[PDB]
Image 1: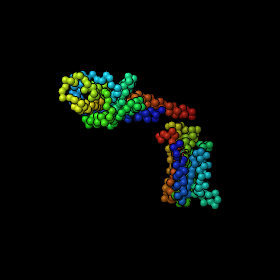
Image 2: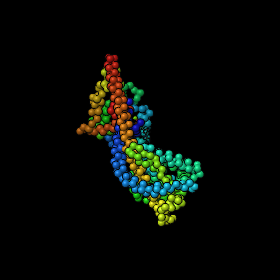
Image 3: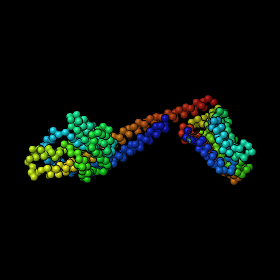
Image 4: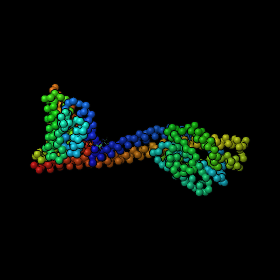
Length: 161
Length: 271
Ligand SMILES: Nc1ncnc2c1ncn2[C@@H]1O[C@H](COP(=O)(O)OP(=O)(O)O)[C@@H](O)[C@H]1O
Ligand SMILES: [Mg+2]
């Protein structure tokens, strides 16, 4: 309730419209209502063209009513799209990941039954390094760039979670 | 909850720091206050020496009245303003009940604030920015001027202040102020010479100024002391709460560690 998605919407408007580098939006376990509203607001703002494709944003959506594995891998799907647009296209890509804590908590939910002793709070033993293998693919190589705007859910406004 | 207790602890800690600093500065001011009070006390009592040695009984017939109340513009001193308030309002009630109209001056923003919605209809003038700086004679000259330029020539009057007894106790005193008419009528004044309307007028005006000055000095002192002891009490109580909340914080953090450990253990035992 602090304004993360409206902030990422302002950023989408301004940046993704003022950019020529094939942005990508990965919806990691977020509300279907907000995803539909974002889709329909991108369409009418010309960023997505249903006819004579000149669109400049690719959307990936794994939403809340999906199992934990889907919400854990949808960020990697968005990563893979942006990684194509950087590796084999030379472009400077934008990657709006919203929300990444859903990726982490989906990791928690997979570890729950994956047969592994839980770490602190309740997350997996494999949180830091798995989120790290994910977050290290987001970088500027000599081939291209991927600047990533990541909205991150802080449970109970803790910031020490 | 650990974070709730953490926030409340930090709040009470900085509050205790604030009250300790206020106690320190209030004692620092009270030093100079009680330094200046004694010569001013000799002075302001030598002024009243005549109305003592003459036994001016006071007007038993006259109708109107003027009531001055000495306080400051800063609360958080104790029951100072409350004491002046209660005595002033009780006295006004008993004088208006006895058929004697009274109008009231308030030296200090606090007394005007706490008595304005009470007796606004019976109110002459108020003064502010008294209490921050050590009161001087200029204060009294100004207040007396605007007491005289008021045109309200009172039958009689009473100033109410907090007589400084010492560092711990103050007494709400009510000093009398006579008018030209009955100080002239007082047979006791027939022993003094060369007196007529003019010289008694000058003397009464100047004694009004003197008694206001002496009362301000008696009230400035007897407020820094009350503030110092009140801030002492505040810091002590804040540290008591800090200790008890720290006990509860340690209790809660131990319980949190236990609960998370039991979670981890019960999760490991299901495999
Ligand atoms: N321009 C605005 N006017 C009024 N409310 C706004 C505006 N922009 C954002 N908000 C409010 O911001 C709040 C946070 O919305 P959202 O972006 O979904 O939060 P978060 O992403 O942090 O969970 C909402 O209550 C929304 O109404
Ligand atoms: Mg959100």
